Amino acid sequence: SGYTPDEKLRLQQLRELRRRWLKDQELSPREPVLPPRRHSIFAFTHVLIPVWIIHYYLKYHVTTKPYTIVEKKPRIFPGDTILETGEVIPPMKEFPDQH
Amino acid sequence: SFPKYEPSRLASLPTTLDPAEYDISSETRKAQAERLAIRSRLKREYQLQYNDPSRRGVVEDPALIRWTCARSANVYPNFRPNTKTSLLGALFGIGPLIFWYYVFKTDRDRKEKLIQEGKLDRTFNISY
Amino acid sequence: DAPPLTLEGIKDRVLYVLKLYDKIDPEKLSVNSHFMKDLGLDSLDQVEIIMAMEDEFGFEIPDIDAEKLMCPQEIVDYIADKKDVYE
Amino acid sequence: SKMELPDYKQWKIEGTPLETVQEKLAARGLRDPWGRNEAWRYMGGFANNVSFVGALLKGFKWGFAAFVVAVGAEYYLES
Amino acid sequence: ITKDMLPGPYPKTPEERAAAAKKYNMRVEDYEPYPDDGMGYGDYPKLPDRSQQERDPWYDWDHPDLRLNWGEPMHWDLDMYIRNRVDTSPTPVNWNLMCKHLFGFVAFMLFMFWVGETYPTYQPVGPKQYPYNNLYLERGGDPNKEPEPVVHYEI
Amino acid sequence: AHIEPRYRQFPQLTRSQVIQAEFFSATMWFWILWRFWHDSDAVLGHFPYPDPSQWTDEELGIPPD
Amino acid sequence: GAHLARRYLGDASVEPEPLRMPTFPPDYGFPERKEREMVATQQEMNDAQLVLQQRDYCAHYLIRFLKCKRDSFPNFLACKHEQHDWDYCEHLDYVKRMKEFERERRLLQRKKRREQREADMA
Amino acid sequence: GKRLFIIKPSGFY
Amino acid sequence: AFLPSAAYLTHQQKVLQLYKRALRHLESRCVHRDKYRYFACLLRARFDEHKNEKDMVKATQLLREAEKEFWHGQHPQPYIFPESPGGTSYERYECYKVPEWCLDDWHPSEKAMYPDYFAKREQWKKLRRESWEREVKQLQEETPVGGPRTEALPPARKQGDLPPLWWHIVTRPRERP
Amino acid sequence: MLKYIIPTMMLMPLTWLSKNSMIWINTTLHSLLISLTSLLLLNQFGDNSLNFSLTFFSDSLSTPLLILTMWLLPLMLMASQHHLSKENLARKKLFISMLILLQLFLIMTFTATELIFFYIMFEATLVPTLIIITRWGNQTERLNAGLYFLFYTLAGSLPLLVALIYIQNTMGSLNFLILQYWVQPMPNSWSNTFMWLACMMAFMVKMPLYGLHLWLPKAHVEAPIAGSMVLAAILLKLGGYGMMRITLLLNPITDFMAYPFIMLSLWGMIMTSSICLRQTDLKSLIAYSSVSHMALVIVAILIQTPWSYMGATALMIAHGLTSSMLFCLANSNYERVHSRTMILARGLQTLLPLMAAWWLLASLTNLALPPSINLIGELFVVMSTFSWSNITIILMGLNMVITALYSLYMLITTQRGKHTHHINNILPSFTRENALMSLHMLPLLLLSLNPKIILGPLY
Ligand SMILES: CCCCCCCCCCCCCCCCCC(=O)OC[C@H](COP(=O)([O-])OC[C@H](O)COP(=O)([O-])OC[C@H](COC(=O)CCCCCCCCCCCCCCCCC)OC(=O)CCCCCCCCCCCCCCCCC)OC(=O)CCCCCCCCCCCCCCCCC
Ligand SMILES: CCCCCCCCCCCCCCCCCC(=O)OC[C@H](COP(=O)([O-])OCC[N+](C)(C)C)OC(=O)CCCCCCCCCCCCCCCCC
Ligand SMILES: CCCCCCCCCCCCCCCCCC(=O)OC[C@H](COP(=O)(O)OCCN)OC(=O)CCCCCCCCCCCCCCCCC
Ligand SMILES: *C(=O)CCCCCCCCCCCCC
């Protein structure tokens, strides 16, 4: 067995009222009635102004203080020429060639 | 046959395996009808206030106020100092205090003995 | 995603599933065809019809509601009530 | 608007594994009433899906052809 | 809310038990209080200690998030048996069998990591060799001291 | 135009998604075969593993007494 | 990996213990045994900032390879020859370590045969 | 079309 | 057991709930549709064998050991529908189900944004507050002494009267707001 | 300090001569001007404390408590003007007079150069607080809560009076500046043991210590919102201030007298956080959270390392702002649902999204999210207690786990889940409420930028 006739009548009436409610939930074609209110600007305003700001900051307030920007010294190989000195690094010993 | 399900405190017995669910006797029918009647009368008493257009507030639950007043405000008037409560108040009240006292006292006596002998390595410790 | 259901589309899909069930001939079937009185089906058949509705529309009908849907119009009305169609 | 559903007569289970299921049920006198509901899954475009070695070797033919072309191009490029 | 709707002391007479069972909106035969061992429960009902997860999720509850109704006597540990917290629902495997299998698996894995620590695998090679007395100055050795010469040979 | 949903049957495909799927499967197999051609050692082996049992005693320094 | 079975399921008296080996002197069995020559200078691999795990006896090929890798930027597929030279010399060092293992294992065999011959004689 | 009204709490304040 | 209308579960309802749980857990065990269809017909045969059983004690015993059968042979992670309780999408959109009375607290500058909606809402609120006293006196004249026995609600009997306690059923939120 | 005492007294004719619709606006405006003026106390030096007169001085410990105190008065006036809207005009002016007078007592409590003046002001702060709780408290329990609040403090503090007059007769002075140079070692004797107890137990009650905290989840709950704000934000910190002054004199006897109280507070921060896990009252949950946070300040004062004092004064300021904001959020829901039960109003983020953002940020500061000064004080106390004993890291970490648990449990319970259906008087958030929340939270977040002004005399 299924519903009683009272339950089917109540579901029918609630169904009609529910569908009227949901149909009233639609918008009008005039609603929402609102009150009355450059191609590469991103790469300017989000990079080129921050690189200016951060480079000014790092150049004249951070690198002016000691050990703030400390850098690992550049790697020196046999054969290199030092720019600060002009000193040429002597190369390695000639290899006991294996193959 | 099949391994029987053994219910635990944190894993209860299912409704489909409970032997008291399949009762057809009239005392269980009257108990379940009376429970449905209580739940239905409380349901009606709720949803008359809940569906009221004039009501704008809190449908106050006396069961909730009754629960919070049982949880806090009625505990001490329903307290009797007896064997069970005194042993649970001594075990759970000063037990851990004595335990952590002897733990931290042992650890600090050991640390102070190693420090005043120069045995604890304290080379770079200058923040304290 | 998720195109809206209409009562026309729900009724067509429900009758489409019930016409693909071998214990119901399609030429007798209508929306008011009671499964036990008219179509002469078992309660096991009604449970299987509800499970085919669940596998068709993708949501579970609970058993307190599944024991009561005894004609296809009741099923379409229940799927309307739980999907809120004709907004 | 109106989504027109296809024919319900076109989903017959002959030629599907539902046929083998109904044969192995009718061997003991059982009959399946929901096979035509399941029959769309095994027919039409969803029929004859690939295996797993057919799944891994998708694009193997064009990839191996491009490999032949690139090896030939570097063998003709060194000269 | 008023005085005779608040919880009271432990019921001793059956009419006090019936008045308390009427107070907590439940049957007299289903009303059991916590046992009067003085812990401080009063006449509050001992509900059957289930989580709210076991409640019927398809029933139209008055509090659908909590699976609880209005006027229903709450469990003493209702804040504990919420669905955000401790679940008491029936498990497909027994509790003791779960505990035995999990403890045995964890104990067996720890025992086998200890055995494999006691019997480690390696490769049929010697130690890795390093120049300059096993890299004495590189490993922070002081240059005022002179290490023992660690000499490696060809093979 | 967009895709219209179908009922109980294989959906409408775009030519673009099919040629992209085929192109990236072909790119996968071309890259696997190309790197297996040029390297061939990261899978099978870089250097021949020597046999210590076939080593003589003179190169290892084992004096017979 | 059969040597694990020979050390565990057999005896360890003939199998070498990897944490302490060589247990035998490096001249015991070698008349005038030559040393391993270090090609890369200590200051050269100090200035090259090599990892202390990487400052082994074949650091010179690693220095040449890192110099090629720095100098051939951005052509990151340009210096496979220096890399294979460094890998080949690491392979030779690994063969030398295998020779140390087999030398210690055969001298443990020599000590075992020696003490068994001594137990048979005296 | 068939735009539905979205009941949401008062976002003015 | 626990139902809003009935006070118990009948034997027939327990058998049907067992049959549905068994088919769902079997479908979880028997993933492919042809194989599930085969074993589901076998399970239908196992339920149709003891179907015409008129001994209620024998049927109760068969139901009980069939529940033990189902408990021993259930899938540990059965398939749950997503909006079904336990499912991966269950009660997901409850954070978007704002009740209807929150529109009453809007500022008039955002009620002016939807003039026809609130103008059409005021007649719903009017309809509810004229239906209310009639549906209260409808409930008090039909409910017996001692309160209602079941949680069933009676429908409306006259024409022009709305069903009693209809507002929070009709004006409930949608499932996808 | 007279340039702050005199305008606070001039707030009394400002609140009694104001027009009847102007008595909130005028007191709010001029107390905001006093709070602006409070920043002149940041004239601190690395060697010397800012020593004004024979009566008043301010080091870097009293200065953040002063700025927090003078900042708390306009926020208490904003919080307490909605539920006292229907009050009589004379009783409204009496409430504002009790708030102004409590501020007047506190700002010369923290600056007291001499310790018996500190005692007189310190116990003078009971009387407006007692009047506020027992007069403008809401429920029945406010009278009993006023009894507990009065008679724990006086039971602790009347031995403190005898102790301070004994120091006055022995050292010759209770000037703290003189006692910085005339301090003598306090050796082991039973006389000095009870000397230590008489000097410390009043402040242990005021913090509160675990086991003596039973005045607090009734006084903080049964007060009105301005009472709850001042009790959580300043009146617990009077105890830590008095401890950091008075433990100058209690050495070396503190090095073994501290052990029972360190055990009580290290176990009370576990037990009261566990209590917070099972509270049904939201306001009591915030009360036991305050006990849990002040237990760490007690441990940090009793181990008396510099990192511990820095973390303790940072945690006192941070907890003042955070607990005041948590009570104000609790009041913002209590003024809608008229119940302090936490499980009643649920799902409130669906209704009040920006107020739920304020709930989120106050729950994040409660769980000590870095880089807030909550985490700074928490973290420095954990560093110093680890250096004290390495096994205290277990209790500190377990406390942090339970603290995160009850903070986010409070957030999830009140703000998340399905909303309560039968509650329909959930108004939108007023501008007063959101302004109150922001005036708590925005200084608490800006103090993460420059946190050195809340790290005490030995930053
Ligand atoms: C001295 C000059 C100082 C200038 C800089 C100021 C520095 C920060 C100050 C404080 C910033 C937070 C205040 C605004 C948020 C609160 C209100 C709110 O919800 O607004 C949403 C609203 C936009 O949202 P909506 O959708 O419209 O409505 C809200 C939604 O309904 C629902 O809302 P919702 O949930 O969608 O959105 C809330 C969202 C929710 O998200 C979260 O809660 C996640 C946050 C935590 C995780 C991520 C951060 C972790 C920590 C890392 C960052 C700090 C260190 C970074 C440095 C590097 C590492 C060391 O939170 C946020 O978006 C907050 C962003 C900023 C986070 C700061 C940390 C807050 C976390 C808690 C404390 C952590 C430790 C302290 C850190 C202090 C740092 C200074 O914002 C506004 O309209 C802004 C109003 C104006 C704000 C002014 C703030 C400064 C005022 C100071 C005045 C005096 C000084 C003058 C300077 C003025 C500068 C403008
Ligand atoms: C919160 C509630 C509880 C509060 C507890 C407060 C602390 C507990 C201990 C307080 C002891 C009393 C004050 C001591 C002041 C010390 C000053 C001094 O000079 O001491 C050295 C003096 C030494 O004597 P003297 O100073 O004359 O001699 C000079 C010093 N010698 C001895 C070296 C020559 O100590 C005393 O005279 C006695 C001190 C102990 C007094 C014991 C009585 C009180 C017992 C505890 C009561 C606690 C409250 C109970 C009620 C609670 C509410 C119901
Ligand atoms: C090198 C060392 C390596 C060591 C590795 C192992 C160390 C840790 C050992 C295990 C300890 C932690 C795990 C136990 C607690 C787990 C709590 C948890 O996850 O709760 C989740 C639970 C709901 O989870 P679930 O069942 O999945 O939900 C599905 C939908 N209902 O949610 C709930 O029920 C809500 C719970 C809220 C209250 C929580 C109370 C418990 C708090 C536990 C604190 C533990 C503190 C440990 C301190 C250690 C100090 C050293
Ligand atoms: C001896 O066998 C040395 C190798 C390392 C130990 C054994 C590793 C066994 C697992 C890897 C090889 C698996 C072959 C199927």
Image: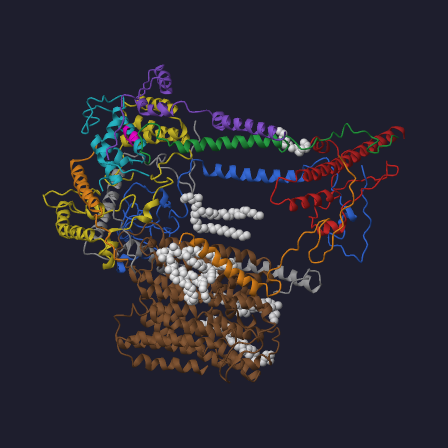
Q: Residue furthest left?
A: I159
**Colour purple, chain:** D
Q: Color used for chain C?
A: cyan
Residue at horizontal 27 percent and vertical 60 percent from the top: E3
Q: Nearer the viewer, residue J388 or B6?
A: J388
Residue at horizontal 54 percent and vertical 68 percent from the top: J310
Q: Nearer the viewer, residue A58 or F9?
A: A58
Residue J307, percent from left and from top: 57, 66
Q: Residue furthest top?
A: D27
**Colour brown, chain:** J
Q: Reply yes or no: does residue C52 show up in magenta.
A: yes
Q: Color used for chain I?
A: yellow
Q: Is residue J63 above or below residue C60?
A: below
Quarter-wise, where is residue I68 in the image? top left
Q: Is residue I138 left or right of residue J8?
A: left
Residue G116, percent from left and from top: 84, 30
Q: Is residue B8 above or below residue B105?
A: above
Q: Which residues are magenta?
A: C49-53
Q: Is residue B95 left or right of residue J72?
A: right
**Colour green, chain:** F
Residue C76, percent from left and from top: 23, 34
Q: Color used for chain G?
A: red
Q: Nearer the viewer, residue J23 or J159?
A: J23
Q: Is residue J272 visible?
A: no
Q: Nearer the viewer, residue J153 or B78?
A: J153
**Colour orange, chain:** A
Q: Color used for chain E?
A: blue
